Length: 118
Length: 118
Length: 180
Length: 180
Picture 1 (cartoon, rainbow over the protein chains, first blue to last red):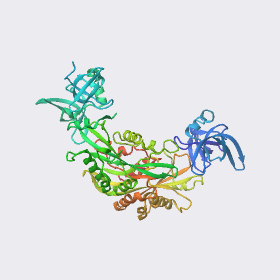
Picture 2: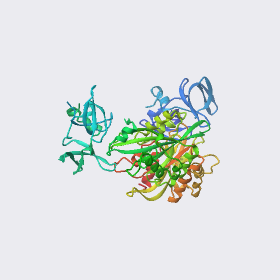
Picture 3: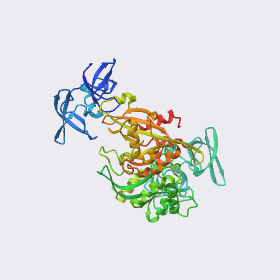
Picture 4: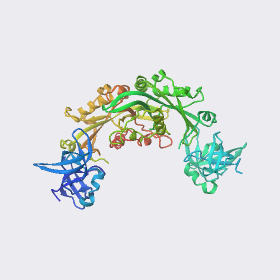
């Protein structure tokens, strides 16, 4: 699991953010380094071993101007040192960086059954 | 008939029960109440407790002057000059209250619907 | 809930009933929040000493010659001298309700329209009113908008601690007055 | 509830994190509510545009040389020029937390002791602040007392809507500083 990309939340019931498992703390305890630079221990049930966020997933996208909105993943584009998601909203599609794509409590819970590490 | 009998009733669906008398049976299971405070309105039988005096060991809400109120237990009745006075025990101490200063909360009055409700 | 009654019926109540008066002071507000959310109207409410939100107003004493004399007196002690530039009257009377609290209290609600300058004037002077820092912890404006998330603005403002039926009275006044 | 992290830990975060700062302003008040309830200290909060209670402050921009610089700047915008009579420094820093919001934001909480005169001036001139009527709907004082009924006062004030973990930051500051 060390070095595997995941999407996990650091608060009791916050959003899931992208990161990697840095170490296996043992007994359902994992230490994660998020792509944003934040490190903390997270429980297996709050981790989604899921990368990339699969197509047709309802996600939360972030814009540079403080706005955020829901959308559907319709494309993946890998570039050197970064992944880009194609998010569709109201018929149109826009590219977002990896860190700009997160999951609300509801959006990530739909993936626990298949991708959860609880 | 119930006309003239003393009762304790709430003029609000989920309000407190206040002392008063039934002034008339206006049909449809409704009874016009003249509360001791001068207010008068039609009240359903379900909101009327045919209970006078409020029996001993009943948990009541005692009203003080100003805006203070507290829960207590009836430990005495005293009728001097027609008026009724209740002796309310609170924290091992007893104090006298006039009839109008003794009311029932929704809970306190619901405990008596079976034995006294109409 | 809170049972309403005609003014006359409330005036017929016995001395065991206490009377409170509260005024809804509102003014036309042409401004906007973030240049896209209309403020519509500026509406003032007080954070009362018990940590609850409510309209400016208070109890009517036996000394006060009438419901209105008492209201305007309370409004001066709560809002400052800027409240003397106007006077709430019987024409501003809206409704009367018996409060659901344990005590016997009938609440008389008034709505008075002011001008943006008048409403801003009482805001600036409330800090030196007799009640500032005692009975009144501060004045706040009512957000009549709803933010993008659907909860921010008025819906969340209605989630605060209010006095009696201030929430229902506020919403009923907004619909009646047609400020929404 | 919100995850606490050290100040250094927060400063080392990637550029994807934004930083906000807010300050609890308090001053000693020898006043007596009703002549029998000590007010003790006067603590200022503000009714936010979203209908929630919070402390003054705001975002830290690139122009800001430090967290404290951005804080004092925001305070001047939200409270007015009376805020320039003092400055919040690193010695007033209390804690850092990650906000529950979707965007990546870290919140820094401060607490500064002022004189009752400095606090009143903030209240007096709060109506002239840039954010009054827009981002700030009004200022309120936190009641540190509990009334005879055991619910009025602080307990009911803590039932209002608060942004983020302001309520928790509030209670933490009441204990650590012995204000209550």
